[PDB]
Length: 48
Length: 89
Image (cartoon, rainbow over all chains, first blue to last red; front, top):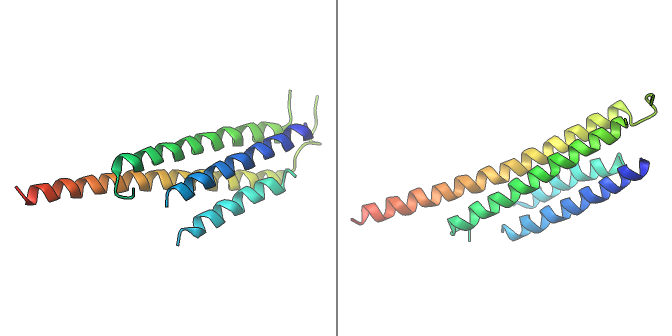
């Protein structure tokens, strides 16, 4: 269950990376990426 | 491509999919945080959950926002393409 939560967080980060690919593909928008990052990082942090 | 409306809408579709994917992941994580099938509150803390709920909601809004903007851009490119051909009747 602490295992489920780590697995989910791993999956969340794959999704985050998937999103970055699309953003790049959709070429001062480096802030979108940074803010996006922050929020995922917050989620990732709290779940380790 | 920021010139190709059919492509922007497609891109919008993708971000919509991303938004759905995050909402479903947030909902699974909620459940896991709560941690239920007697299990008392040894599970995930009240303040961390709030941070998470907020981070998830931000991500979903941003994703919705990119979708909306692409859709509006397409609409805008068509309206102007159409207005252009008219002026040249």
